[PDB]
Amino acid sequence: KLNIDSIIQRLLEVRGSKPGKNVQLQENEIRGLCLKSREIFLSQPILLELEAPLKICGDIHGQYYDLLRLFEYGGFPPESNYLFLGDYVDRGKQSLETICLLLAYKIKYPENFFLLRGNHECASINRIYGFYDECKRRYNIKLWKTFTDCFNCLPIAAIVDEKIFCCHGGLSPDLQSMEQIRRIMRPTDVPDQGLLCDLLWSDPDKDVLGWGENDRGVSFTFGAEVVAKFLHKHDLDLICRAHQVVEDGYEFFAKRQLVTLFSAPNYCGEFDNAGAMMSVDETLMCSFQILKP
Amino acid sequence: XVXXX
Ligand SMILES: [Mn+2]
Ligand SMILES: [Mn+2]
Ligand SMILES: [Mn+2]
Ligand SMILES: [Mn+2]
Ligand SMILES: [Mn+2]
Ligand SMILES: [Mn+2]
Ligand SMILES: [Mn+2]
Ligand SMILES: [Mn+2]
Image (cartoon, rainbow over all chains, first blue to last red):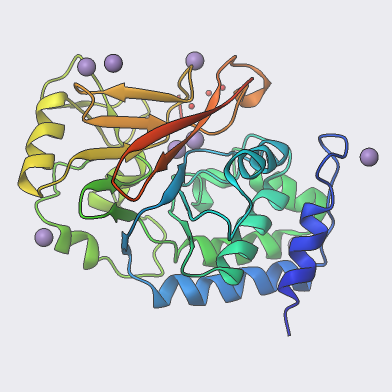
């Protein structure tokens, strides 16, 4: 019933229009995107096991014309396989187009296109930071509630060729095994502190060596010793994460055992940061493509 | 505004 190809065509039609130009999909089409993608999310593991070649992207935050630049640079699906690390909505002016395009590609290419949950794919947060207001202005609050149901089914982590562990935020002091992630049942809002909360919210910090206090008011910070012990225990080579604005779009932490990716250049119209994307090839070589501010 | 503007 859902015309996926026509939705994609209408979303891609504003390529090379004035940045900020809207695509007003019909409410029933947006609801169709949410309900179909949710079904696919639930049929696939909550801990994704993925294989290279793959382009990995960090926070987008509703900067729709920047998302199109990422695809223009990386190859529009299905030309390349993609993993996004979350934070699709809030902050920018076009969360609607942003999330609609990524959900459309998930439906269209369900084995070649992947999306993880970030801390902004959570009703409590997206209420304050822009996505609720955008839905109220352009559609209604019932559609925002619909997105909420879809977001609650997103997977939380990915492992790329048994070697690169991928999540939005970072590690947890309650994380002992990969089974703990697999035990997590969906749909879930994130009502309690603990493992799921930490995977969405936690931050590396060079001035703690173990676990520390997080300035955000939630979760923890983790030091280099933590990253090292984790990568050892589970026989892995790298943590790939997002969640923090960094100047060059990518930044290494903990003696290059972790990388942060941030994919939205000139974040909020305030920072002078680049955005970046990590390309992992078939021989597990990593490279970085930079989007200029 | 720290939730990170
Ligand atoms: Mn135009
Ligand atoms: Mn309403
Ligand atoms: Mn295990
Ligand atoms: Mn973010
Ligand atoms: Mn985040
Ligand atoms: Mn910066
Ligand atoms: Mn370095
Ligand atoms: Mn370091």
